[PDB]
Length: 280
Ligand SMILES: [Mg+2]
Image 1 (cartoon, rainbow, N blue to C red):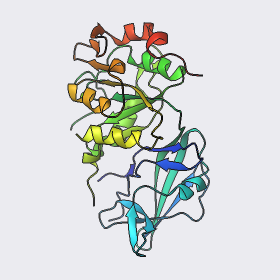
Image 2: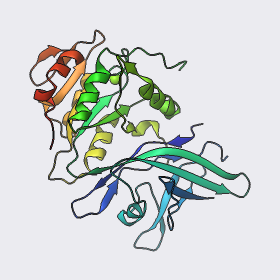
Image 3: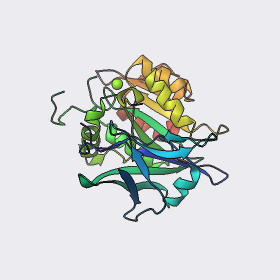
């Protein structure tokens, strides 16, 4: 089974509170309390518990004095993490009297309320085609240079995977291994469609979840890259203007939906300052 943590996103609200996406973490070994360390610093007075199936949650009282199982921590808990802007290292330590201490590592990102995100599907959009693997999937040409320059202009790349949770760590390794003419894929969180995280329209629900951790009065999702018409629908209903949605096919032809224009990652990169203007 899966052992790891799905990249976590945290957003600082303009009242200085903190909101985050749900924590999806699994201890594959453990067949129990859970402590946290952020940036190699243990976090005091914060703990998680674990269900029989291995999924973990923050215990939180409701108004009837019953324990609720939250995947999203309170703002007060998140402030104790002492998160820096951007990437942060996070580890979860599950202590068990039978199996001792078990540790998993992951990534947690802190954005501001005015941070602008650029979504990118993985399969068919980064890879050329949409269980046996080696990471040698083919990659559309010139995509690493394009995304690098989007990031350099102040946007934040956010990747989207609909593969089963078993492949999550593989997808992370595939993206960080891409090298094209010296360019690499900019570091960023990989969100997992909630249908793949079973416990107790999916791409659209995930992106609306991400949008809703930002205040209502800003539109945080600037643009999106996909390869199926359902990717365009997911982005539109999460707040992306049609003009900023790009849909690529297996011949690496990119359609800019708003302008109904045929293009490519190379040509979009040449027009980077027009389509992805630099942010202050
Ligand atoms: Mg796809």
